[PDB]
Amino acid sequence: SRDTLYEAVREVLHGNQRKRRKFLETVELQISLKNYDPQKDKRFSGTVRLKSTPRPKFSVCVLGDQQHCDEAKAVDIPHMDIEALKKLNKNKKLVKKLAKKYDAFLASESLIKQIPRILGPGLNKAGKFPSLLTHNENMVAKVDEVKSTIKFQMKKVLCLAVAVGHVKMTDDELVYNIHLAVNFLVSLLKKNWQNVRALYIKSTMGKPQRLY
Amino acid sequence: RDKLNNLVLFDKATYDKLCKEVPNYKLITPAVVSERLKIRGSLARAALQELLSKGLIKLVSKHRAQVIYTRNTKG
RNA sequence: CAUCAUUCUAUGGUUACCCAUCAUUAGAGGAAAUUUCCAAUAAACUCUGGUGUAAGGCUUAGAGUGAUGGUCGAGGUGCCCUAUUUAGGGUGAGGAGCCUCGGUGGCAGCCCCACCAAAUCCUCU
RNA sequence: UAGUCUGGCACGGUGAAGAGACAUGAGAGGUGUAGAAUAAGUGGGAGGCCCGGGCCGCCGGUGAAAUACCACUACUCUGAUC
């Protein structure tokens, strides 16, 4: 699992010979794996932590009935009413559209319940897992999943793909999202042992480069 | 083997499927009717002279065994 | 009424996690045959809670609704014997497991009637 | 328990032909109703690419994923050998 080449931690600013594209790109990192079973109780599950502002952009939704009335308008919360999650799940089988059109949901406190009725566990097998915490702290607690950890999964195709950083932050911010990513593959280590065979550090869209 | 259950007299729709559509058949015989419309065969012998007294069908040759009628003329 | 789904309610259920089959773990189960019976053989197949993942509302009390105050229509699917093999000759029993408003023939479509089937196997003889 | 039958290790080699692997270095490969399409998949995605100009698409529509746009593991076999 352990490799490391953290003695020459420069030569990442090489921009204009890889980068010449104009849309908003996400630095999405593929790493090479070997010798793992998708069938059995063999797991490749967990959420690798990233405190150093990754900032994933997707179809974002946020709920919560707290002192987040004014705290959540800093980001401009699309706060649809707790009552108005009815057609969220209803225009799904009767109507042939994705009635969500948002790739996250939220669990909140001040009130221990978010919703345990047909609407809440109606999301329980939709994907886009509502897991995040915004219970009692209130520092911002709105972007503290986005600016906090990334999630990944395992499946039947034996391959891994997940984002590490984004294009708005520089190459000296794309270097802060390499060290604190694959050092959590030496800390997190069951005896599915020696999982990392080759490492592919990358832009979003360019050429393959090696740190091992 | 396969026992069949017939009916004594008409249903309202079955007379509208008799009086319209049996004059669209050619063999109007009491053995045709009780196989097709599935009634007690004795009935179909009596219904056809009421249609002659109504004036739809043509008595070709009546007999004890088989009475033979046909649908409406051309002229 | 016994029911699956529809909309208005749901202090109701858990997000690295819940359904219904299939895949498997520990249980509950025979008529014909056979002949005059009896207790037994020996399971096919059905479900109870365990657990898993390609489709998806779990369930739950209950107000208004698709549809029988009886419901689905209900006729087909096998095994064995033959140089009538596009066919002819047999008829034990009991579980399971599926298509269609089927296309062509007749007094032509609907009723009557003919045939070609959607996937059929396990078992005590 | 002597003996004897037998398998392993050892002394213990050389060269070729061969059969299978692994390490490998390229191709080809995918058919549920369906949506215009033999849906191999993951992090995607409404944009980029070439000649201001133009392209495949979005959505509708099939269906937890839907086509252009960086990559790479697997899986059905072929397949070059320091």
Image: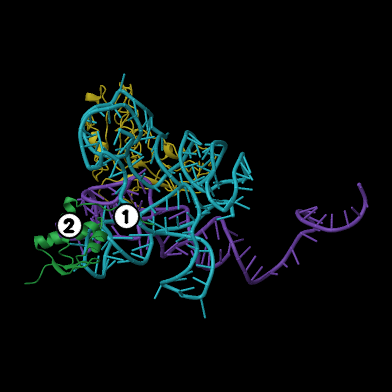
Chain colours: A yellow, B green, C cyan, D purple
Q: Is residue B23 visible?
A: yes
Horizontal side of B53 relative to D54 (left or right) equals: left
Looking at the image, is A210 positioned above or below residue A174?
A: below
Check disc 1 and report its element: helix, strand or loop: loop
- Identify the chain of the residue marked 1, using the numbered disc in the image: B
Whole-angstrom CA distance, mark 2 to mark 1, is 20 Å
First in sequence: mark 2 or mark 1? Answer: 1
Q: Confirm whether residue A20 shows in the render.
A: no
Horizontal placement of C43 versus A49: left or right? Answer: right
As drawn, the label of residue B4 is 1
Crowd around label 1: few <14 · some 14–19 · many ≥20 (10 Å): few
Residue at image location 35% in from the left, 28% down from the top: A133
Q: Are marks 2 and 1 on the same chain?
A: yes
* In-front residue for pair D42/D2: D2
Please state which amino acid type lies under the numbered disc 2: Lys
Outermost residue toward the left in this view: B75
For mark 2, what is the residue? B17
Residue at 16% of width from left, 51% of height from top? B12
Q: Nearer the viewer, mark 2 or mark 1?
A: 1
Left or right, residue C79 beside residue A84: right
Question: Around disc 2, counting alpha carbons within 10 Å, would you say few (fewer than 14), some (14 to 19), or many (20 or more)?
Answer: few
* Image position of A37 with respect to A115: above or below: below
Q: Amino acid at mark 1?
A: Leu
Circle on res. B15 = none
